[PDB]
Amino acid sequence: GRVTNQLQYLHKVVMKALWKHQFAWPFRQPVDAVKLGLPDYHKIIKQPMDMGTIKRRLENNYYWAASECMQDFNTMFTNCYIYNKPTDDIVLMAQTLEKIFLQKVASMPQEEQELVVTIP
Ligand SMILES: CC[C@@H]1C(=O)N(C)c2cnc(Nc3ccc(C(=O)NC4CCN(C)CC4)cc3OC)nc2N1C1CCCC1
Image (tube, rainbow, N blue to C red):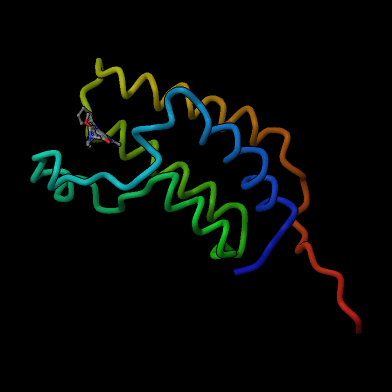
């Protein structure tokens, strides 16, 4: 992938805020459905995603565009809403983190530019 102003913002502003949040801990690592005794998790959730995975991807410049990274964040939250019961606290935890995600995303740089300065 590459490094852009928007990806750097997702890494150093958005991920920094979410990763340290009180509610982050269910989302800092992939779901281990074997240890949790949930054999239906991977039948229902076809694209697992978590903040540990996103953070590693950002660290390794996996993304080409901030929108791909935002889609991983979105997939993470959506998986939560799809699999769990509407009244579960983890749903309100996801909704809390997602609102911060959106509020932080609103102040992201407008024009995506690769953070690169090259000798022609
Ligand atoms: C998968 C379904 C749904 C969901 O979407 N995600 C993301 C999820 C992510 N993580 C968890 N749960 C746990 C996550 C990590 C741990 C953990 O680290 N446990 C330690 C084990 C060793 N020892 C040090 C003591 C504690 C324990 C968990 O069980 C509560 N649950 C999740 N749920 C919930 C499933 C039960 C209600 C909803």
